Image (cartoon, rainbow over all chains, first blue to last red; front, side, top):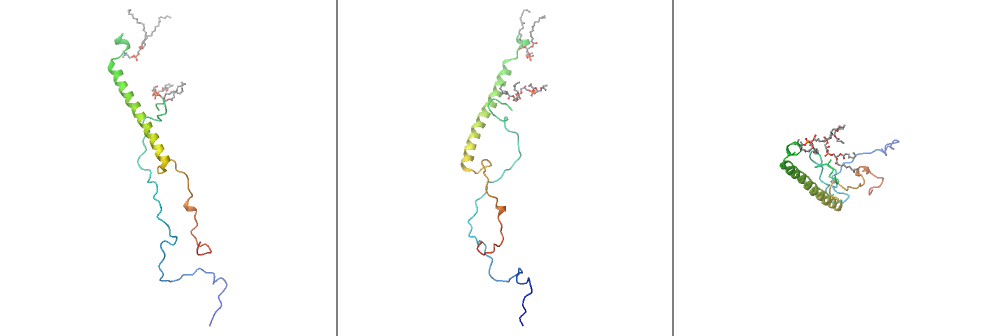
Length: 57
Length: 69
Ligand SMILES: CCCCCCCCCCCCCCCCC[C@@H](O)O[C@H](CO[C@H](O)CCCCCCCCCCCCCCC)COP(=O)(O)OCC[N+](C)(C)C
């Protein structure tokens, strides 16, 4: 009672039921370094301007 | 002559005080900025001197015709 598969049936993406737990770190990755924290707060004008040599603005 | 062309000494005195305060603050800020620049360029942990790295969004996380990538 065997039926030959039709054209395009063996190439389907199927689903499988398994009791094997999904691995959590299959790449054996290290802990990622922490990023530079952030930019926060409101922007205020530069204190005393550019402060470049004699310029007061 | 004093009444017509000149002010009292207090005006020049206190204007000098204000000018000195501004200039001293500017000098301190310049020294602080130089120190911050040195530290930021040495460590690379601040907003400045951030050099580009590869974007992680370019990686394809798909099965690769081989189980071991
Ligand atoms: C009376 C005889 C005995 C005494 C003689 C004394 C001689 C004094 C006269 C000579 C003039 C002195 C030189 C002027 C330098 C002053 C310039 C400046 O520093 O003064 C300004 C004052 O401005 C004045 O207008 C100065 C005008 C002087 C200009 C001289 C012009 C003379 C030209 C000659 C023309 C004659 C006829 C020409 C025919 C063709 C200050 O402005 P201001 O922001 O308020 O300052 C605030 C101070 N306060 C609060 C006290 C007011």
